[PDB]
Length: 148
Length: 148
Image 1 (cartoon, rainbow over the protein chains, first blue to last red):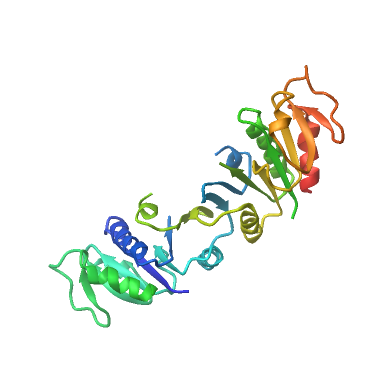
Image 2: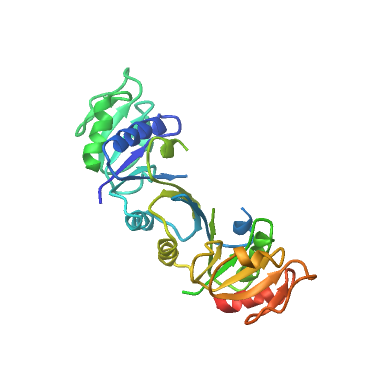
């Protein structure tokens, strides 16, 4: 169940990056979920509430939640794969967006498969992975290839 | 996996009825779901998208959906039971809210366990089930007893 993550400080360009990937996955019939780490019936005390109509479900669910369980949820709704925007602490392969060379320090994490540096004044060769500009299409294509 | 439904025309008082039931289920530690029959990542083409944070998941999922499958979803998120507002065509026990005696005709369905008539000028003895006023607490308590 392939998983790629996108991690980065606020305002790095994560949503735009993710949008490009998702647009390109539709066109390829790739079946790909998306997960972002961040009222009456809900207010009267229900934990799990939803609306469904014309093939679209809108669900709010108070648990219990950690990443493993969110992934099982995605398996259960029968997606092929999963793009996650955040949970840097997770062990899944991940693309790191840097707004500045010194972002990489505080973004402490494993399984980093690429870096996107937003400024090209300071994209120092970093050992052991490839480096793109933010707008390079190869970087979106690198993500899809890992998603299959 | 106990299930009760609430069915009725628009403006019968269904939400209010449901609210009373849900409020009373919180106080009893009853673990009860709620289901009502009726954007960037979603727009770029993803079918299954979500946000999670501080133990609350907000999920939008384009399928495929019918009632059986929505129920399995509820089993999977580990609720004890389920209140549904609508799907009159389903076979689950159901409470019918009438705004007028002639509502019952067009509300064609099975497994009706109670009727709430909103007007008391015309609540004719109807064979084979009990009859309440809209504000009667026994009617909310009747639903909870079937939910367990």
